[PDB]
Length: 313
Length: 317
Ligand SMILES: Nc1ncnc2c1ncn2[C@@H]1O[C@H](COP(=O)(O)OP(=O)(O)NP(=O)(O)O)[C@@H](O)[C@H]1O
Ligand SMILES: Nc1ncnc2c1ncn2[C@@H]1O[C@H](COP(=O)(O)OP(=O)(O)NP(=O)(O)O)[C@@H](O)[C@H]1O
Image (cartoon, rainbow over all chains, first blue to last red; front, side):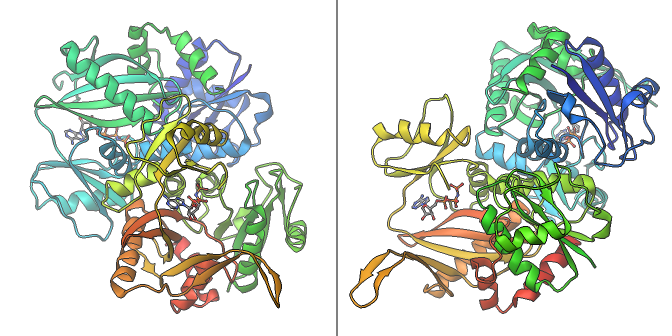
């Protein structure tokens, strides 16, 4: 049982990706090899991979995609990439073509969960509450059936790259234009406030289990934003906490997710809304997902072992 | 401009893929090379590819994936594969990594349109009419909110599809279906129904084609003639009153735009009781110069080479 980890990626979460590879590599209960995708798309195998894993960022790589890697040597591949070319289904399909079992969501589920429009349409349809939104295709005349303020962000592009809060219905044109830079389609969502953020993790294939529920609170700026808190158990009557968990498990089911998902929720005026499912969350031993499950009773090592095994069932 | 055509595939539509590549290869108005995926999953390049085409069926290939192809030599990849590793978005996903512009639907649209459950959900939420249905996942009690009869097909695989007359039979159709896809759909058996087809062309905002109709003729023994095989009839255009033709076409365009499909699509509908029901969207249909999609567009005034030309050109958006 040998495992292959692919960290890095061409997305803005590159550094965090390598940072996660560090945690996994250290506490993973399996002989594990590393492979790195440099910011320039080139791959780094062998020791160059780890040398980069030690530098906290891999500006450039050696092998053009597809890399001359020895997929033969591995039973399971653990992708740790974010956003575009990470959890959008592209890498997953590559793996399907190579016939390699892999950790996490498959093609379809990664692509749906990555697109802010289609995933909302599926969840809405399935009874999961989502924020009132609208999709705006490039060249299509905007039509917001609700008043500002609101959020505009490209349909499917990880990290807040291209997002913006819009106050005046007039400035909506600037928002779209910006977002259009990273995607042909964009979403306009009714901005909530007051608003609390709740996080919950899921483990398992299709019918997974939910970890306890946690709340993300931000501390004052000090200009740098303040340290985000990870309150858990989150301060919600047992009622809403359960509701949040069953809602996540339900969304996890209809979308056919596999392995894991960091499900984010918005709590505004007593109402819940599922913001998004992250098929590949941050994996440092001190990241939101592993910390959530540790609280649920699953050690970092055990969590990784269960994930890798799941890639085979 | 240089185009790379990829046909064959490990799926059951392997043979039909090659015939499509044949038509495409004979009329495409651009220099085009052929790459073939044999049934064993190994690729055939250059001459071997073209030779596999001649025999119509490539049992074995020479190169394990990924193939040693000079992608750089091409401006657009036109993938002609049906089903698994064809419309599911894996090859499309592989092409995104290669950064090559390709013909047809992207990863999401391809994956989504390929799923008989997720696609209906998105279309329903969009107000597009679909046949009542419910999804059932292996090892989970079925909760069919509607009375029989009804069809049970696997969610992502035309095998395993059975017609159920009585509930006591559902467990059988399900078990039957779960031997292909971990997920299946139970649809309300609509009767009587007329099948309607319309082709869409363009990226997201397309141009519909004339509506066509499919009718089956059973095999029979003729007095003078003798045996006469079963037959599928493609009536272009469909014998419908303008209002229905109008609706079915706009309905096609509506669904095409919601799903964000690119390049092309053959949209199928069921007409029953005067109610139109969107059955499914095929992101990569047959391309024989006599397949429904190409014929539909000929009727619509777009010659074959022209249809091919526009498809390729759209790949570059
Ligand atoms: N409708 C909304 N109302 C209030 N706050 C919002 C809303 N939408 C987004 N936000 C805020 O913006 C933050 C990031 O939005 P988010 O969609 O999670 O970016 P993202 O994580 O990069 N999505 P993705 O690109 O698919 O991974 C959230 O944590 C919220 O604090
Ligand atoms: N709800 C229905 N009512 C009446 N007839 C149906 C219904 N569903 C399917 N059929 C018939 O069964 C045939 C095949 O079902 P169909 O779903 O079109 O196979 P498919 O297009 O290959 N999709 P798949 O089930 O994934 O293989 C259709 O051409 C119809 O004639």
